[PDB]
Length: 102
Image (cartoon, rainbow, N blue to C red; front, side):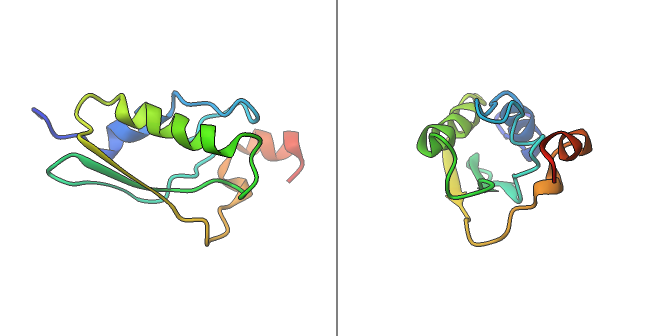
């Protein structure tokens, strides 16, 4: 547009970040619930993890945020961590439900 980031870009930016445990990106894992961007390019996301575990959780949070702040428009970054709801293991490719055993 001019200086107006969108959820479309935020997803496609996040497709870069791959969790060294899993070997897929967060859009592949389908994690991301909401994505809203204000007129002030406050990129806000309701992204969550699968589990409150991970192998290096904090680093993975910061890696998603890394891709998000690399959008060159992304003035501010309102990364919530909504851990309350049950994510969904079938969000991944169906090939990987076969692979992992879901």
